[PDB]
Image (cartoon, rainbow, N blue to C red):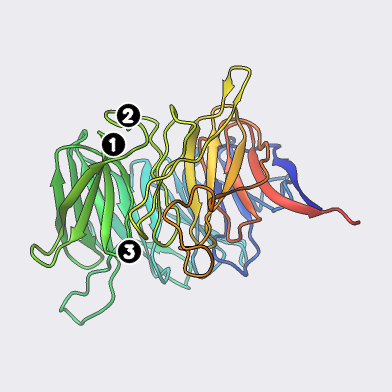
Amino acid sequence: MEIYYTTKISGRAGVIAGWSKAPGYPSLLAVALSPNAVGIYNEEGRPLDPNNEANIKNVRGTECAKIAWHPLLPLLAIGWKDGAISFWNAEERKLEEDSKIHRNTISSMTWTASGDRLITGDENGRISMWKTDRLMRPIHVVAYDEPGAVIRHTVVGLPEEMPDTNSQVVVAFYVADAQERAVVKWCNDQGYSGVVVEMSEGVHTLVHYPERDQLLVVGSSCTLNVLTRDEQLGTWVTASKMKFATGTGEAATGLQVAWAGNHTLASASEKDNVVRMYNFDTEDNYVLNLEQDSGLVSRVVCLAYDDRYNLLAVGTTDGRVMMYKFNQPNLNLEPVLDFAKCWEMQPAFFVGNRALAMEWGPFPRLMVVACNDAINVCRKTMLSY
């Protein structure tokens, strides 16, 4: 067979792991190192540069908060915990740091579609789409203050086409979450921050369903706030709101709403060994059982989806992260309402500790379960017969 290898990034490894998520690139797992560096590490479960000089110590010498790689380049945007937006390229080995506008700890950092800007934010509510150039500098463009609110959840759902020049502008659906006052708002990189929605309940996770245009927000009551940019209202208002079947009621703490396929929504909880998939294909909910090991009960700590290649990560309390094979919406074989048996059990692997931070790689073989013990590189190595 071809058996998974449990090989772990260590040496100076921290918690936040950054994959070159674009396929076809040298998928260098950047690792937010504890001694104020970001470890640009390889994919064999080893540090690529254990000396950690090409792995870049912070110019301002702070701990990292967010590392995200360019969708069209091996450019790594490092959000350090001072506002230090650090653009570093793997092909250039140049880290260029600008901290003119951003001064608080980088809270929201999401790459744009083309990587021409970068939705940057901090705890001041200052969301700022700093432009990204091939001239390799993070340069601030637009400024939006949300005082009393933190830019916590910021998804890229529907890029609104303004009539300014009909340009496809990334419009960041950021939540002005002023202490659970989930003021989800949409800001564009030119001049404006419009309000997406005003829910009283805070955003548990800012999921977006693109097939039927549903900003699948979860309120902090396990309520799937199905926000659709309605044909009758225009913005992502709560068209429907039903309770998740995983941790029914007030169980949003530990609730795991990741993705589960093209027309399937993932739902699970830290009190549930059953992992129910809100299958949007034919409106299905169906459990996926887990195990208990002499009191080491495996209940879902983290769900994450390889939406590039349709695999669901199921992190558990015991530490293992087994995998769920989402069989396609069955138009090829056995058209079924219950995909619980179709959601095939995959060979489990023990990455180590409980899955707290998680980041799927560009391929569903190369991946990190960025647990706190080590930056758990997930990979496969062949065994010849």
Q: Nearer the viewer, residue 129 or 72?
A: 72
Q: Earlier in the sequence, mark 1 or mark 2?
A: 1
| Relative side of 231 to 57, left or right | left
Q: CA distance from mark 1 to mark 2?
A: 6 Å
Question: Considering the numbered disc 3 on the image, is that residue within a helix, a strand or a loop?
Answer: loop
Which residue in the rendered view is the most extreme toward the top?
Answer: 295
Q: Residue furthest left?
A: 232
Query: Which of the numbered marks, if any, corresponds to residue 210?
Result: 3
Q: Nearer the viewer, residue 97 or 27?
A: 27
Q: Tag 1's secondary structure?
A: loop
Depth check: give the residue in front, 239 or 107: 239
The reply to whether the C-beta atoms of the residues labelled 3 and 1 are less than 8 Å apart is no
Is residue 361 toward the left or the right of residue 206 in the image?
A: right
Q: Which residue is mark 2?
A: 251
Q: Amino acid at mark 2?
A: Ala
Residue 341, percent across and down? Answer: 54, 49
Residue name at image x 16 percent, y 51 percent: 238
Circle 1: residue type = Cys
Q: Quick check: marks 1 and 2 in contact, CB under 8 Å?
A: yes
Q: Quadrant of residue 186?
A: bottom left
Residue occupying the far right of the picture: 385
Q: Upstream in the sequence, badge 3 or badge 2?
A: 3
Q: Quadrant of the C terminus?
A: bottom right
Q: Which residue is mark 1?
A: 222
x then y, percent, for residue 169? 28, 71
Q: Which mark is residue 171?
A: none
10 Å neighbourhood of mark 1: few (<14), some, or many (≥20)?
Answer: many
- Please say if 91 is above or below 247: below
| Residue at 31 percent of width and 52 percent of height | 154
Query: Would residue 56 be visible to someone looking at this image?
Result: no
Asked if 290 appears above or below 230 in the picture, the reply is above
